Length: 195
Length: 187
Ligand SMILES: Nc1ncnc2[nH]cnc12
Image 1: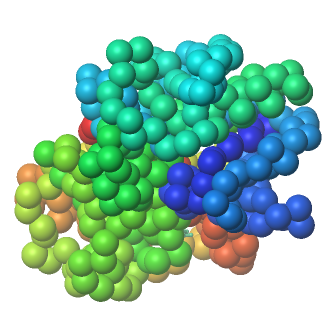
Image 2: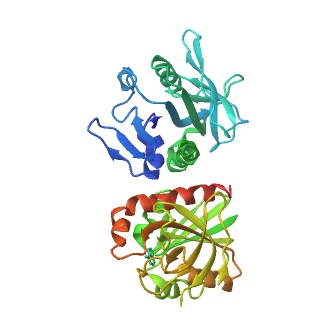
Image 3: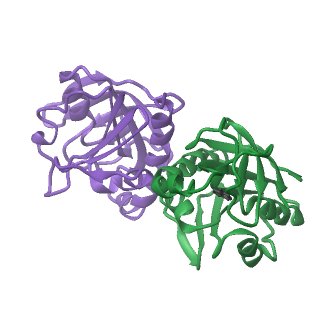
């Protein structure tokens, strides 16, 4: 029996995927669905408050066969069109006050185009950048927690906004469309693990 | 822009497919969704069988590039397992028309009847429904290709509907999981 964990940063990202299957809330306060040989669970990191906390995935969930982090990401290069779904090859956490970085490889999803991801704490609205592609908040954290349970981790990121002040309105106004692109990319993955 | 019409005979059969996209309700039982490249419309009949087809699809809508009739079907041969999604190659009325198969689905032939068929397996039948023949006839009027997705929902023996009633969610979800990739085939 194949056990797949989906991880979304927030409810908006998760919404359309949660519509795809008849999930139920379990007694542990997260969403679950199973059929045939597949268990499909969903966890949402930040449902409350102004920020996510480390205990959202600490200790990391044990026992799954694959984690997929699906979410929105800002485009920091104008050559990335919006509303486009990518899979991630590597994710780096960047600390802007020191320029110190860490970086982990992640497992690409078949048939999605490849991109690099940088995770940063604060929303990225500085502008465009020579050496950034997609930018999110939680990707590195999730990949690093996955390493603690030796579970492979893949990422699906949809381009949600250009990383400028003016560009944030597009994210504000297109959350349903963006969440739908995530759902459409997740389905063929789920389907490939039916035995 | 590709234009797809999906037709379901009742809301329970349609329910999980309608959960797949953030459809807008244009009018009673008529749902619409689009991206730039694909228009996806869903019609749910207001009653079953030939009467419901006539009410909803006469006149037949023009302008679509494909019609898909998705629904529950009875299995009239014990060699057909239940909870299995098939695509249809031909359809006839028990009392014939080619149908366009959806790729990567098991193949079956369909017979459309005007009353719930419970006569057992004593005929060379495969899957049995109430709407498909009549929907294919309407699609022909507008020279539109027609495909059908039929999930085996009961055996055509007495009280066989109990399996369908117990498995409504799973059956409706099987239809949704066959429909979701078709939408993606046009992007
Ligand atoms: N047994 C049956 N007869 C006719 N139409 C059906 N649709 C589903 N089951 C059926």
